[PDB]
Image (cartoon, rainbow, N blue to C red; front, side):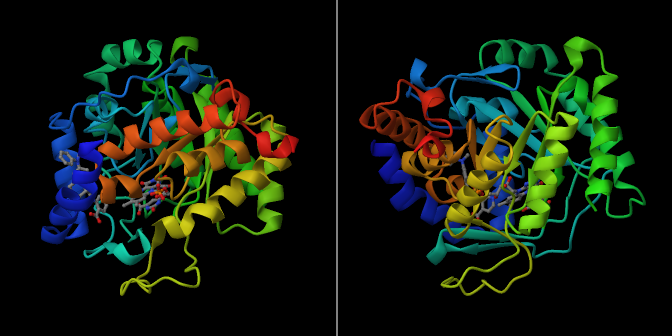
Length: 356
Ligand SMILES: Cc1cc2nc3c(=O)[nH]c(=O)nc-3n(C[C@H](O)[C@H](O)[C@H](O)COP(=O)(O)O)c2cc1C
Ligand SMILES: CN(c1ccccc1)c1ccc2c(c1)CCC[C@H]2CNc1cnccc1C(=O)O
Ligand SMILES: O=C(O)c1cc(=O)[nH]c(=O)[nH]1
């Protein structure tokens, strides 16, 4: 498209050249929230529809947590063409997060490093924001555009389980799915924590009862992954989000800011994330839905995660470089690749590498 090339080659580089990454983030949220966006003319085909987590998703490409931390831009993100929106992380009480600067761009690597530290308006502010559009969301969800809420914990919390429990009670009734991050940059403690989360979820009225997913880092040992898969199956967790940012620094990063503290996102995370999907799919015998995330910026990227075991994918970093046209780009390329490889639709491709 003309927009894709123009955004990617001219507009987005100029905007990034003018604005530090955090300022750029804020501007993007503000523009999205006001619907000041190019016209998303890609109409989603039936091939892209997925049914998972008790919901219909008109397409499998979502916005990852962190872009819209406080639930300010949900409708604009649907307008951009995302098949689903995840907001958060939201903490129980408002908190400022880490001192600035805390977001860094690695243009040479198509990567970002962030150490925001869960800057959050808090549950109560986000609750009121979602309540203001609750019925609009119900219609969107019914039309195949679900909403996820990522729950965090406060810096000073003396018991993580209570922070997450509070999030379930307050935002669970407003979400199609909730996410508990065991990922932000004993199995018995994870079992305790997730048991408490599921109990709180099960205590919500049936029309207000969300799916619960666990979001993991790519930095886990083999033992950690085995332990997570075991607990997820034992307790009946509804899904996994794979992955958060990495605290590793893969060999070959060129950006001047590569040694900044924080989570690395984007292209250097891509295959690490895909491999983690592949492993978690196998450890859960393909019975636990996975949302695949990390360094997706093309149809090929999306399909590699789907074939590795993802039912859905998310992106964030690619949006910062390519702008809004990236969403339609990924969807269109994914559709073409599905046809080329002989799949009837996304559904047929989920986990296809494991049947090879
Ligand atoms: C600036 C920034 C902030 C993020 N904040 C959050 C967050 O609050 N909660 C969360 O679960 N993930 C957070 N993430 C991680 C993303 O949701 C995603 O897992 C990761 O960036 C990999 O996807 P990407 O390579 O497409 O960006 C953040 C990522 C970035 C770049
Ligand atoms: C929504 N949108 C839009 C683009 C054109 C026209 C109308 C809308 C849009 C989407 C994305 C963006 C911008 C604008 C403007 C700043 C650039 C990026 C955001 N950048 C970051 C975000 N989080 C973290 C880091 C960065 C970064 O730059 O390092
Ligand atoms: O808020 C943050 O700093 C944060 C949380 C998280 O899960 N991932 C990330 O990259 N940043």
